[PDB]
Image (cartoon, rainbow, N blue to C red):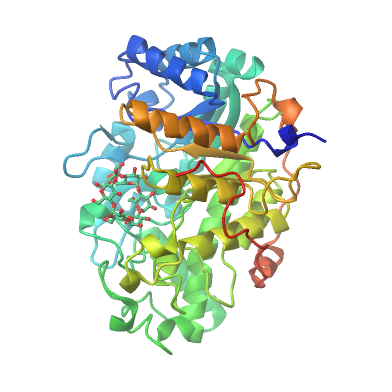
Length: 491
Ligand SMILES: OC[C@H]1O[C@@H]2O[C@H]3[C@H](O)[C@@H](O)[C@@H](O[C@H]4[C@H](O)[C@@H](O)[C@@H](O[C@H]5[C@H](O)[C@@H](O)[C@@H](O[C@H]6[C@H](O)[C@@H](O)[C@@H](O[C@H]7[C@H](O)[C@@H](O)[C@@H](O[C@H]1[C@H](O)[C@H]2O)O[C@@H]7CO)O[C@@H]6CO)O[C@@H]5CO)O[C@@H]4CO)O[C@@H]3CO
C-alpha cells in the first residue's frame, strides 16, 4: 500500500526529425536544454521514431546507427528513459509538411517496377507510406520478404544498441505496423484529399490482396464475389453509399465475408511481425508495444464506417478491438491507443463521433484480456480540459488510497515536445498534469517502486488460432468510468 502504487508514468514525444533525413543529429545543444526542462518537470521519459528510411537508406542491410546512438546518449545523460518506435513508414510529404522522411529509396525503386507493393484504393492510387500486407511474405526485395526486412532491422537495432538496452534506457519497443506506425490500412489519406469526418476508403486493391481475396471467396463457395464497388469515396457520408447504408452490403453475407477477410489481414500482419520482434529482443529488459488508431467518427451510427475502412471490424454487436488485445497477449505486448483526450461535446454533431465511448470500449477490452494498455493524445493540446480527460482515462475509477487502482493505464505519451509546450504558462499547466498522473507524488526514478519493473522479455506464448481470436468479438460491457477525475489539474 501507497499512493505510489497509483503512479502512471508520463513520456514526451521528441520533435519530428530530431535526427534528419541525412542521418545527422542536428542540434544536440538545443535538444539538451529542452530535455533538461522535461527532467525538472518530473517527466519519466521520451519517445522517438527510429526511421527505417534514414537508417537503411543506402541499400539492403546497409545500416547506420551512429546519429541515433548520439541521441540515445544525450537522453541517458539527461536522466530520462526511452520508448523506441521501429518506424517502417513515411513521415510527412504533403503540403507544407515540416519534415518529409520516405521509406528506403532502394525499396522505392522496386515499387517503380512493381507498384503493387503499395496500398491501393479502387481508383488505382498508390499510397507509398508503407508496404502492403500483401507483400509480407513475398521474396521480392532483393531476395527478402517485407517481414524479413522488418525482422533484420530489429535484430541490427538490438545488436548495435545493446549497451543502451543492457543499461535500461529503453523502456519499450513500439513496432510500427502500418501508416503512422499504427496497425491499420491508410484509409484516410490527407494527401488524397480526405477531410474529417469522412468515412475513408478500403485499401485492398493491390494485386496481391485482390488475388488473395478472390481465392478465398472461391473457397467459401462464391468465386464470383468481388471487392466493394459500392462503398463510395473518401469524403462520403455512409448513407450516401450502397455499402454502408441501412441494410446495405456490409450486412450481407458477401459484405460480412469481405469485412472478416479485410480485418483479419491486419491481425495476422500484427501477429507475424511481433513474432519477429519477440525473437529480436528476446532476453532484453524491454516490453513490446503496438499502436492502434482511435477512429471515433461514425462510431455513433450502426455501420461504424471509418473504423471498418481502416480495418477495424467494430460494430455494436461485434467487438473488433478485443481480438487485437487477445493476439497481443501471447507476445505479452502493450496496446498503445493513440487517442485519449477528446470529448464527444467537442465534436461536430454531424460527424456522429464517440471518442469517449470508443476509449472505454478499447481500454476495457485490453484490461479484460489482461494486457497492459497505454495511450497518446492525438492532437496537440495545452489546456486543462484535455489534460483532465487524459487523467480520467489513465485511472478510470480514481485513486485507490488503500492500494493499487483496480484499473490503471501503463503509461501515457504526450504528443510533442515543442517551444509552445515550454512556453511559461503552458509549461506550468503541463507540470500539474505530470503531478496528477503521478498521483501527487514526486517523480520516481525507480519503476519497481511503483510496480512497473521490467523483466527480460520472454518468448511468445503459442499461436492462438484465428477462431479463438475471433471469440473475442463477443461484445462485453465496458468497466465503469468516473464522470470526472478525482485528480484534476484544475482549470
Ligand atoms: O499531420 C496531421 C496530424 O496528424 C496526426 O493526427 C491524426 C490524429 O492523431 C487522428 O486522431 C486523426 O485526427 C482527426 C481527429 O481525431 C478529429 O477529431 C479531427 O480533428 C479536428 C480537430 O478536432 C479540430 O480541433 C480541428 O483541429 C485543428 C487542431 O486542433 C489544430 O491544432 C491544428 O491541427 C494541426 C496540429 O496542431 C498539428 O500537430 C498537425 O497534426 C498532426 C497530428 O499531430 C498527428 O497526431 O496538423 C494539424 C492540422 O493542421 O489544426 C486543426 C485544423 O486544421 O480540426 C480537425 C479536423 O480538421 O480530424 C483529425 C484529422 O483531420 O487524424 C490525424 C491525421 O492523421
